[PDB]
Structures are given as C-alpha cells and as structure tokens.
Image: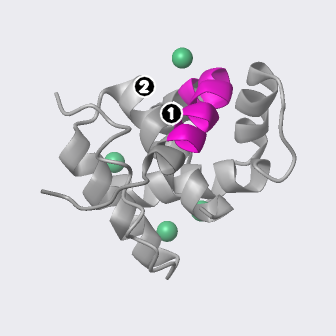
Amino acid sequence: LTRTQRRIAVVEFIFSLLFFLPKEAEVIQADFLEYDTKERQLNEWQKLIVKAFSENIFSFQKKIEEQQLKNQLEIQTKIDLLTTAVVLCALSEQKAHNTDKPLLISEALLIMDHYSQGAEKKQTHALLDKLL
Ligand SMILES: [Cl-]
Ligand SMILES: [Cl-]
Ligand code: NA
Ligand code: NA
Ligand code: NA
C-alpha cells in the first residue's frame, strides 16, 4: 500500500467515529485493531496516528472549531464531517510523525479528491499545521 492509501484508511476510521463521540483513548486504539482487514494490513505507522488522535481529539476539535470562526476576513493584502476527519488526520499525523506542512496539505487535498468532496478550499488550514 502507498502512504496515501494508509492515510485514507485512518481518515475513513476517524470518520466512522465522529458520529458517536466521545470514546476513551484506549477504546479507540482497540477499535482500530478490530478495523483491520486483509486489504488494510494496518501497520504501526497508522496506529501511531490513531493513538495521537485518540489522545488529543478534544483539543484538535476545539482548534478546528475556532480556526474556521477566526476565518472572518475583509480583504487580503459549515465544515462537513468527512472534511473534519481529513483535517483531524493531518493534525494527528503531524503530532505522531512530525510530517512537514507542504506534504500534509497536498496529501489532504489528494484525499478530498478521492472522496470527490471538491471542498478543497478548506485547506488543512495553513493556519492549523506548523511548517518546520
Ligand atoms: Cl484506497
Ligand atoms: Cl479503507
Ligand atoms: Na508505505
Ligand atoms: Na493505535
Ligand atoms: Na499524544
């Protein structure tokens, strides 16, 4: 599997959880194990993202909540749950693996295309991730 496919697997997982939150951190981590299949071949790289997600979901969800709002501009001189799941994965991944900002954003937009969301305009906030 490609790193992109592995990212998609985390996104879909997170997505399925956002309908029924909150769950305890170790519960989500154990739910991720039951989520594994022949095709997913879930590895430690993905499990570390889900671990960061499980332990920081309250803060990530807050940071998101407030960045959207803080986007209230004049000049320059309703986020959905799939788009949220994509953004939380990027936050989770930068936390677990310290992936650089440019790679995370391109990848995120690539996943949005995969789900034919075409709401790419809500970048992975150039505001929410750190450029190293
Ligand atoms: Cl895939
Ligand atoms: Cl999948
Ligand atoms: Na790989
Ligand atoms: Na995990
Ligand atoms: Na953590």
Question: In the rendered view of the protein, which quadrant contains the C terminus?
Answer: top left
Q: For mark 2, does the 10 Å Cα neighbourhood hold few (<14), some (14 to 19), or many (20 or more) residues?
A: some
User: Tag count in the figure?
Assistant: 2
Classified by dominant secondary structure, the portion drawn in magenta counts as helix
Q: Which residue is mark 2?
A: 96
Apparent side of residue 124 relative to residue 105 in the rendered image (left or right): right
Question: Which residues are the magenta region?
Answer: 52-66
Q: Is label 1's Cβ within 8 Å of ligand 4? A: yes
As rendered, which of 13 and 125 lies closer to the eye?
Answer: 125
Q: Magenta span has 128?
A: no
Q: Is 27 located above or below residue 91 in the figure? A: above
Q: Is 1 located above or below residue 118 in the figure? A: above
Q: Which secondary structure, mark 2?
A: helix
Task: Residue at 38%, 69% (x, y): give it.
Answer: 121
Residue 40 visible = no
Spot occupied by residue 64 in the image (x, y as percentages of width and height): 54, 41
Q: Is label 2's Cβ within 8 Å of ligand 5? A: yes
- Pointers 2 and 1 in contact (CB under 8 A)? yes
Which kind of residue does numbered mark 1 sit on?
Ile
Q: Which residue is mark 1?
A: 49
Spot occupied by residue 75 in the image (x, y as percentages of width and height): 24, 62
Q: Magenta span has 59?
A: yes
Task: Residue at 35%, 28% (x, y): give it.
Answer: 97
Which callout, 2 or 1, points at the residue further toward the start of the chain? 1
